[PDB]
Amino acid sequence: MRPLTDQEMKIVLDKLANYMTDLKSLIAPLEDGDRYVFRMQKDRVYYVKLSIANIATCVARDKLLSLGTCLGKMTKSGKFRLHITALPILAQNARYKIWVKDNGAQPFLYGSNIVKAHVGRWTEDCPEHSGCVVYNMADIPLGFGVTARSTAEARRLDPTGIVCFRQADCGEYLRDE
Amino acid sequence: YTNQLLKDICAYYGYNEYLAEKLLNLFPPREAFAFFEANETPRPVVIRTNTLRTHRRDLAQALINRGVTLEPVGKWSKVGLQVFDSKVPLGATPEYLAGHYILQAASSFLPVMALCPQENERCLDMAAAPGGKTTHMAALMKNTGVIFANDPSKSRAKGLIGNIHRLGVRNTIVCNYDAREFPRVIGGFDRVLLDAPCSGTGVICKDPSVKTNRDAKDFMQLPHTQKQLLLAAIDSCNHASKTGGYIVYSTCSVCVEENEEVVNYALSRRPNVKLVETGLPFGKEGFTSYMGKTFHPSLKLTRRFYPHLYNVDGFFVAKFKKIG
RNA sequence: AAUACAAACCAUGAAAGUGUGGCCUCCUUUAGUCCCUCGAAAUUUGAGGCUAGAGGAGAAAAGUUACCACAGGGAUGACCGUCGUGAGACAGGUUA
RNA sequence: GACCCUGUUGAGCUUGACUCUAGUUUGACAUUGUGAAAAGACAUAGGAGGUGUAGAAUAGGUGGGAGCUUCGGCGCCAGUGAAAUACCACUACUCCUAUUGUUUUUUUACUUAUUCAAUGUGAAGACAUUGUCAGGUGGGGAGUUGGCGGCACAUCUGUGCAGGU
């Protein structure tokens, strides 16, 4: 049992804030004083409350498997990964939102990339390589990814081109069964 | 004769001789013949919607438009529907992929309505292998509180983490402990839920191996195994709290060696445990004494579920309250 | 080659003959003591203890894969690029 | 081309020592009172218990015993049931009433515990709060890393059998 170290919390908050706008709102002193303190286990990070950590630090490390909700894991090279497990945290306070239609969400949930015919409506001032969160017509959080280009270049490109690159979806839920 | 009926049942249906002797002693032959017809008949598949995500008439409208035949399951379940036919596969539909509902049986419905989880409560589930049991308390409590879930195996541990994060509970800690090791290490839980593993005689349509692969060593070890589970269950529960917590014991067995005998041992050993009415509409009365063994006569409130009167799986539920 | 046996040789004794080259070898996986303890069980088992067959520089990062992508070596439309690496694109390419 | 090898990247699986301990931490204890309102459990005296099945029957259970008989009712026999009934001896608990009382718990109110303001008397107030152990974690911090000869002698411990020089 250990917390996030200096560089390890730096890269974690680097990749999080690439998709997050208010990191202050996620981890803040609440009414009861409990805080959303980060936590990692078996090279896999988690997002828990402090009072959750106290009632979980009583346990041997090998017996514990997960804790709270998961955010991602670290590779051998040290880069950070954010998973579809972090989607309810991610979609709660999302910066950039892209909405795809039902005939385009089905290839998105299968594992295919986002096409211009898939999206229904759009956000504004989206840069070329900025992160974004993918929604449907009914504001159901589907996934996340990095767009291929900016907003203005998406208007002037062919409708068959790839718009936003698909990183994760609910197929990991279907894979683990 | 009794021996002639036992030989005719074992030859025609394929049950073990010792298991058929137990079932013939448990029930009258007219009830046993309906039992042998019911458990060989496949059980219906029911759908439990996510109250944190949508409501019942919204999902019912969506699945009707997608082509799924639906029917609500009585008046005792406002959260459940029953599936008759579906042109679109249930696993590939957008609602299940988003996490609007989950698939379960009627046995997975009951012990969570037996519990009454409230907001900002501490709950335990020492055996939640399908993962639908832990989700429903989060659906009832509206994602407020702390939940602990225990699992013995890694294969079903990776199975449920795909289920809970699809459903979006966000506050349940799942792990790989021993349920006997749970109260000594952490303890101090307001509510505890136990789905004790057993022979599985209640559900043989899902598990056909129970018909033959149950020897005399099995009906001695598993009742002793769940005996230590309920001893761990009563040690985890708190006697006093701001919101009244309870112990809920559930199993998928129909024999009396797994039902109303273990809960009699826990009641006799610990006087601090009291059993109350579980608030359940349909069920069967507990037996005061079955095989030369005098149980406590307060077990009339303990409920049972049988496959022939209702379209449910074989099940058994008990509720307890701690005093000291 | 070792080993068994036989013969030769050798030591001693004057001869008669005799003579020689032992017994052993912390946890994890497994079985027993069903011995002792804790339990269950209308009398038989479960978990520990005990016994005996076998294994074993430390937080900086490592080992390994009939595995994936890329580049290179061997054996029998296609490139130099620029812009990103979690995936890719190009009115950029030697002529009119 | 398949195929084999090398370097980088992912998917991984396993390891990343031993002993304490911070960070911690689970449960219980005392500080922690005084009244009112209640509830539960233990002291009692009593009314009544008892079906999963079948058995005419709602079978506590135990020991005898086959008519004490007020009657041939039921005992007996006989099904049916793990347990069979007449009879007279015992005690296990349960659903309750009341008190002939002991405790425990929750809420409210007040300050007498606790803690703050002033600082050389006041307030919040029995909520917090502090101390004590019985457990758990701890990679962060501290310390560490093929053989047996032969009692064949003398002196000491043991204090013939032994051990040490």
Image (spheres, coloured by chain):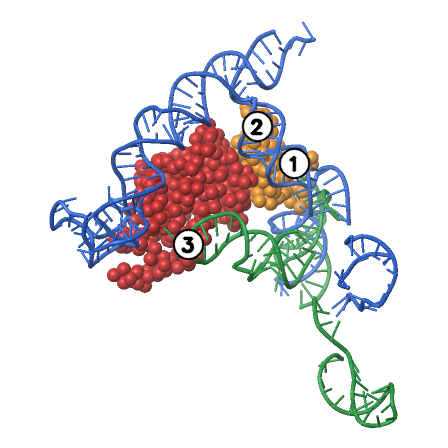
Chain colours: A orange, B red, C green, D blue
Q: Which mark is residue B56?
A: none
Answer above or below: position of C74 versus B34: below
**Front residue (pair B5, B311):** B5
- From the image, tell me which residue sits under label 1: A4
Q: Earlier in the sequence, mark 1 or mark 2?
A: 1
* Residue B93 visible within the image: no
**Front residue (pair C54, C95):** C54
- From the image, tell me which residue sits under label 3: B219
What amino acid does circle 3 point to?
Phe
How far from the left and from the top, in percent, is residue D127?
Answer: 52, 22
Residue at the (32%, 44%) spot, across then down: B288
**Front residue (pair B58, A39):** A39
Taking C54 as reference, is D34 left or right? left
Do badges 3 and 1 share one subunit? Answer: no
Do badges 3 and 2 share one subunit? Answer: no
Q: Secondary structure at mark 2?
A: loop
How far from the left and from the top, in percent, is residue B285?
Answer: 31, 42
Q: Chain of mark 1?
A: A
Say which quadrant the N terminus of chain A sits in: top right
What amino acid does circle 1 point to?
Leu
How far from the left and from the top, in percent, is residue A167?
Answer: 57, 42
Task: Choose mark 1 or mark 2, whichever is in front.
Answer: 2
What amino acid does circle 2 point to?
Asp
**Front residue (pair A84, B288):** B288
- From the image, tell me which residue sits under label 2: A34
Q: Secondary structure at mark 1?
A: loop
